[PDB]
Image (cartoon, rainbow over all chains, first blue to last red; front, side):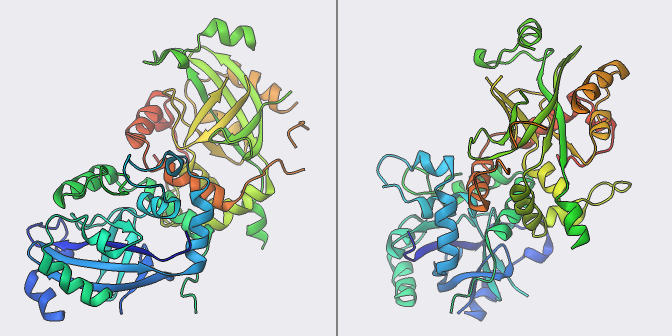
Length: 207
Length: 219
């Protein structure tokens, strides 16, 4: 469980038009700019790992991150054991993985904060199509996305191939109540799941 | 530290455990007035039906015109301290309650997290994210009278009945809470996937008229 956990997904979809103008992120700007810390919902006292790769592809900006913080993984491990959702396990093929499943359930989205400053794991991203996919092997995670080509993965593989977490369970729990009041949280996540062709039938995605 | 102390003071919670005017689709959730009044020592108060998460006790239970109403008291020092620490790391709580009300981090976190009531078969009363029976909105407050007053359906007669009960030292209490922050965190992801959580909660609030009053309810 405490072993590293990889997370991948789109930080932005070019064909997607943001609601707020501030979330506009065109291809040329992204390509022009192309390690970023990985934190929990933009709280820089909650860094859990780092972005291990970023690739601008046909449909958007894809990234792969690695959750390495032992403190964070341990807190997650303990919490996962007290989750009814986690206890239900994944769908038929995949084998149970409490930590990966808790992470899939709690932080189902990605959020690129451009103050690029950091990638935050959050309950749902503010940009659509930013579903977060967790797994123990980065190849497997990248393979969860149909839009990526072999050439796309080669570029990503080339990249990914003191505990920074200064928060606690209390902080994560305080974050959880905020998550319950995010409007259209599940519909957004399902929309994202649809847009990137990821199913619960071949991943740990809970939405 | 002084305010920190107030935060961990007792929290009362009130609301209907069942609405006689609501017909549930599932038979296991049926709870008729005659059955309630017949069955009608303090019941334990727990978090989402977890025996290892008892946070207090029920201080009053009353069958009134519109359903079964109950009042409970959250007393566990450990649970309250956990909640206090988490409440300070919540954007929702930072925004505060509707104007006139005094901010109360602990009361607000409880109002946001465990907005529903769920009566288990009487064995216990559980604070949950949303109850399976409709109209089971949970209302938190520092004083029993105030909480009871948030419900327009209760008459002066109804309150006098409840009051007599809570003014009356339970067997539930040292600290009965045998869980921790990790336990509550684990449970919080479960709540994120309950279907139509917010709509149900808004329907509940309007059904019991808590909308017509001002409270710490976040839904």
